[PDB]
Length: 213
Length: 214
Length: 53
Image 1 (cartoon, rainbow over the protein chains, first blue to last red):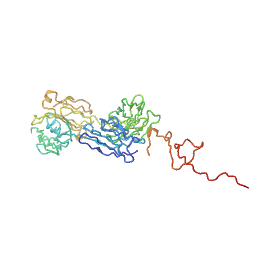
Image 2 (cartoon, each protein chain N blue to C red):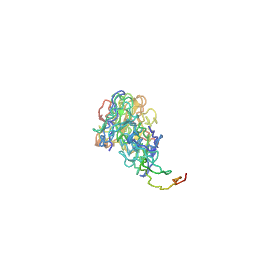
Image 3 (spheres, chains in turn cyan, yellow, brown):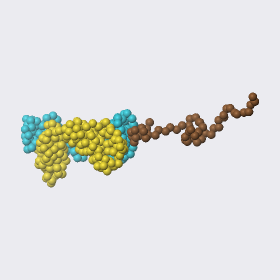
C-alpha cells in the first residue's frame, strides 16, 4: 500500500527525547497506513509501540511512542535508553496491504568493552573425537562487538582452516568469536595447539586452545 | 496490551498448514479487530487484513494475505492466523495488528512460521573442557562445539541447561550445513566445578537436552 | 486530503462544504445557511409607480 520507506533510526546517545522517524515513500506513514510506530524486535516488543503512529502503543517505553512527526511516523524515542534500543519501524499495516516501515532503529549508549574470555578449547577428547579435529575456541565478551577469530592452529594464525564463528555478544554486549581450529585431523590435530586470535578490532588474543601435540 | 503474538516460527514445510497463532492478550479482540501481519523481523506490519473483528467487514490487506489464512478469533482473543497451505512465506515473525474496526495498527512479540523442514541430525555438543594447554583461565573454556544438528535449533549450554556460564555459542553455525554451534561456554573455572559443567545442547535435531561434561 | 479508515466505504463519510464568498438572500427554498449575516440592503432596480396612459 503506502510504502513506508522508514527513516533508518532514532539517534540517541544520552537518554533524550528522540524520534524514530519512519518515512513513507508514498504518503505520510500515518494512522490510515497504521504505521503504529512499532518498535519491533524479533521476539521482544515486536508490537505496535505506537498506536497508528499517533500514541504510545504496546511495545513502547515511550520510546516507540506513536507520533507521525512528518511523512516519517516517528516512533517517538522520548528518553531513549539502552532498553529503548529497538528497530522502531513504524510498521504500517495499511488498509490495502501492510506497506510497513522498514526500520527506525532507536538506540542509546550501550556495548561496554568487556574482557574477551579465553574460552578456547582445543581439539579435546571430544573436540578431536571426530575424524576432523576441531578446536572449540572463543573470545566471549570481547571488548568491541568485532573479534575476527583466528584460532591459530599451532599458533599458526589460522584465520583459515578454522571455523571462526561470528563474534556475537556473549554476555555483556560484547563479542564472542567462537573459533574452531578445523581440519581433517591432518592439520588441526597436528596443529592441536590453537590461540583464538579474537579480540576488539580483530585483536590477536592468546586464548590457549593449545592442544597437546 | 496487544499481545497477539503469533506462534513461534513453526517448521511446517511449504504446502503445509502452518498456524501463526497470534494468541491475543486482553486487547478487545472481540471488541476490536485483530489483524494478522506475516512480516519479517524488520519488514514492517505487512497485514493480511485490516481485520475488523469489531466491524462487520474485515478490510483484507494483501501484504500477508495468501496462504496465511487469518484464523482470528474475536471472542477467543487469538489471531491464530492459521497459515493454511502455507507456501514458502510463513518464515517471518507474524505480527498481529489490533485492527480495531479495521485499523490494523498493533502487533505483539509474535512468533512466525517456517515453511521448511530440517533433518533431525545429532544433537551432540563436543564439550571441550577449559583451554587445552592452559585449562586455567578467568572463564574456564567449557567449550561445546555442538555437533551438526540438521535442525538449526542447537540449544547450547554450559551445564545441561543450568547456570549457562558465559556461553559463547556459535549461532548454530552451518559449518556442517547444520546446527554446528561451537558453544565455547566459558563457564568460570569455579563455575564448572561449583555447578555442573555438562555442556548442554538441546538441539531440536534429535531433540535432547545434552549434558556433555566440559 | 485527510481520510480515515473507520469507513473504508465513502458512504457514511459526510462531506459538507461551507461558503461565504459572495452573498445571496436566504429563502424557504434554502436551508439554514451557516451565515446569518450580511444584511446588505442592495437596491431593487425598478419601482412600481403610477404612470398615465
